[PDB]
Image 1 (spheres, rainbow, N blue to C red):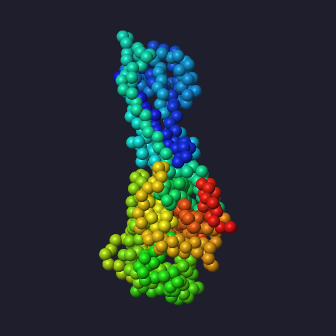
Image 2 (spheres, rainbow, N blue to C red):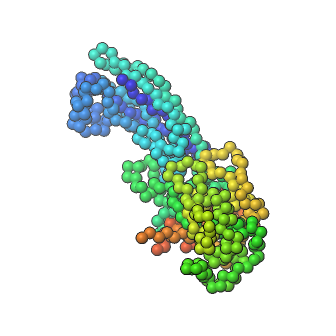
Image 3 (spheres, rainbow, N blue to C red):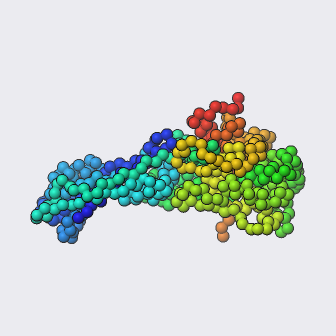
Length: 493
């Protein structure tokens, strides 16, 4: 008959060459039952080396004595298979298969994914590039002589073609750092889940994408689906104040607003017909445009939104990628939602402006802050190593981008700003947020550094630390280590 020859699945490395998924050869054992039936006295020794019960093994050989080929076991270790082969039992033959091994384990479990018992990809990169990584299986022909004995020198009908190598955009050094500090932030704040994304704002490469809780892809025998979800690409949420800078970009591009314009926010609430907009910091009477970001004033950005109209705000969000398909082709990836109505009443205009009228993923939010950090130039996302700068698209003018960049640095360094997120030795820009979802609380921070010449954008999501500024220190530590890892010279002395 015919026996398939499994193809060596292509190697997955990080951007530097660190192995992330390796096809390790294993030993699979198959038997010719008619040949096995002539050496019954060896079956107990055989079943022991295979790791099978003596009687169950004997039953299986009898019930399949008619066939010329059955599998005894698949995927033994090299030493185990050599134990079986050392018995020299008639009718027992071996083939070399491959088992996928993930050296980093749970650190990069969601990005890389994992494979079948048949070594085809089921999640992550392993599934998104499965065509690329799989290769073609070969065919071996079982030749029997007279009296049904398999010929030792097997006959290969068709050769297997190996799969192709893939280098991800992930940087394993930054992946470890992000996986570590995010893991600490949850066990310290007693949080349920979380996510952390790091992007190269110039290349669009994804330098790290870690989720908690995670799982070990080498030990899936008790895998729980709560750890298998790639939250960075699947969990959608209302971005809240983290998309206020993109409302600000619309206001500065309208020509009707300058950073020094004041807006009346007395008394921290605002009545829009039957709805009531509420600022958290109601102890403010008037704010300029930077202060509206510093204080997360829903009232402040709503009055600006009424002036410039929602379609201009919708346009900046759409063009920085929010609610749009990322093009990564990852399985289970969610596009989120940007609201679609032709006419924009005041309440819909307001909620969109302060980030409650839309749904985004953490990956989209990092992509949006990368465009802002890249001087308003949008570059496509990439999970594979880019062979250097791709063509970007100017979606925010460089001067409006520089102005909002400066405002976001003021969110971190100015009076009343979030001093938590400061990277010691560096100038960091960023914006915090909070997302609530009702069914009948996520801490958000998004930023980039160094603000004098941005290199990387980061988004930190931390699920349910209370029944929320817990993400800001996570940004601080990871951004510090990341800059100190990929060697960014300080800009704050």
